[PDB]
Amino acid sequence: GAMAPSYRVKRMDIAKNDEECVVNAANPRGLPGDGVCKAVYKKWPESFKNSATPVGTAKTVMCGTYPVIHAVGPNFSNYTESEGDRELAAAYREVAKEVTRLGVNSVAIPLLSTGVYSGGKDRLTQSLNHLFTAMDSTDADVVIYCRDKEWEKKISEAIQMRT
Ligand SMILES: [Cl-]
Ligand SMILES: [Cl-]
Ligand SMILES: [Cl-]
Image (cartoon, rainbow, N blue to C red):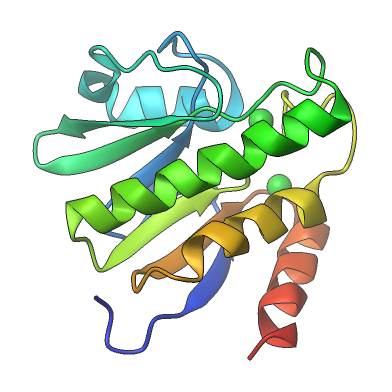
């Protein structure tokens, strides 16, 4: 574990992370996709060998020795608010199991279901609170990656509210 497990947020491309493993905002089919998924495919294409996995699950594939945890959040265009909420919480619980099994001291994570899978809603608080529910019992340093300036501020405030 990290000596004093922490949460941090950075506004930059998760493909440039400084952590021991990365979480992909994957699609269920292991396709290159859009947004964060396409950035992950450009940096770690080898990790998309047999990465297909269902909604609400995570599947780890190595790129060399570097673990890529493909986490499949629900697309709120297709799911009801109720069933999507359940599957989004489930994907983060599976990320926490994978981070624990790998023995890493740090992980780079994007907010699942906040981009092309948001169904055109602002899901920062919903997605971040399910991230915390899963990751709070882990001892990895967690570094959340975002791209919007206002979201960086809101994520940073939310981390500070609990310290
Ligand atoms: Cl960047
Ligand atoms: Cl998304
Ligand atoms: Cl963002």
